[PDB]
Picture 1 (cartoon, rainbow, N blue to C red):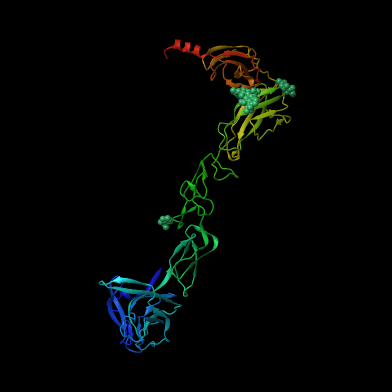
Picture 2: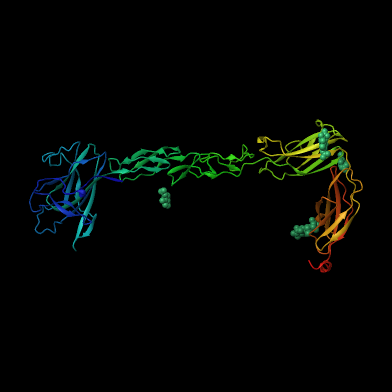
Length: 525
Ligand SMILES: *[C@@H]1O[C@H](CO)[C@@H](O[C@@H]2O[C@H](CO)[C@@H](O[C@@H]3O[C@H](CO)[C@@H](O)[C@H](O)[C@@H]3O)[C@H](O)[C@H]2NC(C)=O)[C@H](O)[C@H]1NC(C)=O
Ligand SMILES: *[C@@H]1O[C@H](CO)[C@@H](O[C@@H]2O[C@H](CO)[C@@H](O)[C@H](O)[C@H]2NC(C)=O)[C@H](O)[C@H]1NC(C)=O
Ligand SMILES: *[C@@H]1O[C@H](CO)[C@@H](O)[C@H](O)[C@H]1NC(C)=O
Ligand SMILES: *[C@@H]1O[C@H](CO)[C@@H](O)[C@H](O)[C@H]1NC(C)=O
């Protein structure tokens, strides 16, 4: 970024530059490269001998600059072109500067020689130029920049020296260079003026942007002479609850539905399932009411809840020993840390208040924290009634203000299994089904709850069998082959347990033709 301390082409009416001697430089109206009409200076005392012609600019405010740049546009007539020119002819001019705190210059001060002044360089027409048409004849306009520093006083003058040439100084622009305010690696680096030396790299310190915090230190950026910042050093990062936006220029609060817990430039991630943001810019998602997240739980994981009760409690009692199996709860709470607890309630044979179970009762594998849906129960009071409660508990249960969901079974020791079921008859049949029924076993020995039926193809074996559960003593079996003989065995279930499978009974589906006859009679639908 360049800041102009003086521009000769902004001259409204006339530049006030001092000419010494007046014999030399003269001010003349001219054109710029775009043919806009400006003020220029010229000197062509080529034949005259021993010429030292000086042109001094007005006072120029430094305005805090450190290295000053002077850009010069000009044209020179080549001494070859001038007929019968002496060897005094030159195609160069010299640039000088004088530093001062106040515009105290006269026609005699400072002295018009090299030393009160300071030489920048000898300027010549060298390969950097443009060509502009004027009225069919083209003019060559050279542009040359020079720089000088350090500069310390409030201002300075520039001086131009001719020593016997034909030249036209068209424009002079004086400027310094600054580096603009920038945001890099999360930091605001403020305006920095370029340094005095040509190769200067000036250092500036970064401060974190808005809702951001320093992460890697130190935070530094460097400004070069051409007005450009270099590669950054250090880093600021958007703090928790804030995400980097607008090519890293702002750190913005996390939008609703999103959270961020640790510092970073990354973007906020959505609240896990069954969680929500109380507000914007959230460091955490609050779990849904009745739902909790556990310690040691990944925070990407959804909020979870307690499991429901176990179901399908099936009990088989062998004398004082017992076996309880079941199937897992309908709702597992979203967790895989689900385990079962068994609580025992020894109770009177009648409606007397239940008592605590004995110390002697043995639980294999254990009373609590069961992994499989089954418990094998050892020594227990014989001919005694009891209630067993199997509760389901998962890894978030300890946060629940409610008691665990459980399943209950009332059962009595040394109770007899139902007798084997007598016989079964085929009620109806189709090509793919067999509907059949059987009699209640003659000696239930308790209340019967459900039945079990096992079927397999006669050509195949019990190895290939299937088993199903029947709430009543009649049921349909579907999916069978056409005209095939199937072997059926049935078993009853009381709280005490299962009976013995009945004798293998042999039924058969309709063949395809028999089913054709049946449906043909049934016509129409
Ligand atoms: C009904 O159940 C029986 C027994 O479970 C099944 O028979 C078994 O079928 C498998 C292939 O499905 C047989 O394994 C095969 O063994 C031969 C060598 O004999 C080998 O070349 C094959 O790559 C394959 O490993 C197995 O031997 C056989 N077992 C018996 C005792 O026969 C039968 O597939 C089941 N059918 C249905 C419809 O479910
Ligand atoms: C399992 O046994 C318990 C024994 O405590 C039974 O509990 C009683 O249930 C009746 C049901 O109306 C209540 O009126 C009683 O107050 C309960 N307490 C007692 C001490 O008897 C329970 O009903 C039995 N469950 C089944 C399905 O038989
Ligand atoms: C961010 O960078 C992309 C790069 O293609 C540019 O198109 C966009 O204008 C930049 N936005 C801002 C605010 O600088
Ligand atoms: C019950 O357990 C005994 C061992 O204590 C075992 O011999 C018997 O086969 C089991 N089953 C029945 C129905 O008794």
